[PDB]
Each structure stands twice: as structure tokens, then as C-alpha cells.
Amino acid sequence: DQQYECVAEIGEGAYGKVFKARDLKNGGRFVALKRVRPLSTIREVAVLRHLETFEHPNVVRLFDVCTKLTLVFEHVDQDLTTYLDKVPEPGVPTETIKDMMFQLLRGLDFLHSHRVVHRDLKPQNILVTSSGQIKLADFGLVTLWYRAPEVLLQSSYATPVDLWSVGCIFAEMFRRKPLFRGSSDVDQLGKILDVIGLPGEEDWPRDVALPRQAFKSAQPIEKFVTDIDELGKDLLLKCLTFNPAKRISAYSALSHPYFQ
Ligand SMILES: CC(=O)c1c(C)c2cnc(Nc3ccc(N4CCNCC4)cn3)nc2n(C2CCCC2)c1=O
Image (cartoon, rainbow, N blue to C red):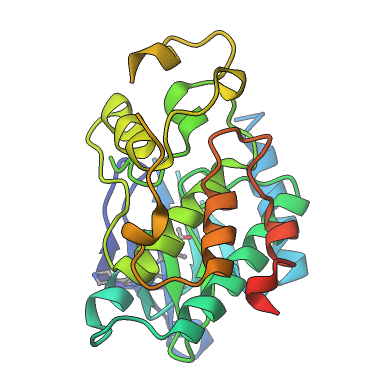
């Protein structure tokens, strides 16, 4: 659009490239824009232009949709990735991990309550403002490291998909490196079960291509996620529960003694 001007390139990918641009009309503020190169997809934008009306403090603001499209949003300074890349030793402060995780679950509880699933939650799209405020981005239409077991298996794809990704990002917050760094669904699933263990046959998805009988003893987490309290250990384990039905929800997670 002519109401905006491209200065730099934020990110590239299959979904299309997003750019940092100057919103000349609105006091030359920095805005993030992404193009698109038509009936059941009308909903996607109707849910976002609606989600917008609640202006949740932990989700990127949308500014406009122009025409073949141009999507303008709020520009955030950096992501969680480059945030972790610059934090001095011995990593992120206990309280900084606990705070940023709250803002993450709030934005997740907001999206879930409004029947929205992120589906691709990674540090690359968990943005962080100058003030240090978490903003969820890259939703309302690679790296399997954050993919949930059931997505990998191709069974369910419901809201517990993001609670796995959050336990993966919660670990990476301490560790400062991906917990499960697989290279294929089968490799990912593997590396996952090498840590959490083989779940009971009762929790394995009934009727899927990959059987339980194709993989492991449960390993303690304090080994892989170094200096984490028994409370954070309790929360992250509930986040990383094989059975999506047993996996904690952002709403019960927002309650947990870890934030008390
Ligand atoms: C489509 C989006 O929701 C969206 C928005 C609105 C956005 C806003 N500010 C960003 N701000 C950032 C975040 C990081 C950078 N750097 C990119 C170059 N390397 C250093 C970090 C620059 N700007 N980045 C944004 N993204 C990126 C997240 C991952 C994919 C693109 C987005 O998807």
C-alpha cells in the first residue's frame, strides 16, 4: 500500500515474507506488513478483526487490511530468539522466566477462550518489546522442535498443541537451547519419548500410522532443565504430558503455585 513504506526484511518462510515498514501517515511509526499472493477463509480474518476488539496486552495489534493483500500490524523490537541470544550468563533471571511465562499463558488463555489455536508456537514468533512485554504473533493464516506429539502422530490438533510448545519454550528459557531438537516427525517423537518416557498403551492414540511398539524409560527433568524448582518442574511436566487430554490448559496453568 502507499500509506506505508518497506525499509528492512523481518522474516522469510513458506507462509510469505514479513517486512519492517514506516507508517508515514501515522507519524512514521514502525509497522510490520505481510502480503498474500475465498469463502471459508473469510472467517480467519473475521476472528482476528474480532480478537482485535479485546486488545489483549499479550497479542500483536492489527492496524489494517488492504488489496492479493497487505496485512499491517504493530512492529515489535525483537523476538524471544534474539532476546535469548543477547542475555548475559548464567542466562535469564528466575523471575524474568516466571514473568515472561505468565504473559505467554495469558495470551494463550486469551486465544483458546476465543476458539483460536496458535499451531506454530516458537521463540521465533514470541515477540518482546523494549519494556520486556510478551506479544504472541504469526497466527490467522521447517522446525518440529516445538511440535506436540499428537500433531507429529497426526491424530488430534486441538488447543493442547500450544501447551506442549509452551513447555518446550519454558525449558529453552532456562537451558537457552531447544530441549527436543529432532529432524523429522519420527526423529522428534523419538527425542521426546527419550526424555518423558514411553507413555502407557492407554494414552497412545487409537488408530494412527506410528505404533507405541516402534520406540524408552522415563528420564528425570532436573537433568535436562538444570536449575528449576519443584514447582516449575511440576508445571513444565504438566505442560509436557503425552496425552493432550491430560495436558494442562493455559487457564489452570495461569493458576498453578509457580506464579503465587
Ligand atoms: C505476521 C505477524 O504476526 C508478525 C508480526 C506482526 C511481527 C511484528 N514485529 C516483529 N518484529 C521483529 C522480530 C524480530 C526481528 N529480527 C529479525 C532479524 N533478526 C533479528 C530479529 C525483527 N522484527 N516481527 C513480526 N513477525 C515475525 C515473527 C517471526 C516471523 C516474522 C510476524 O510474524
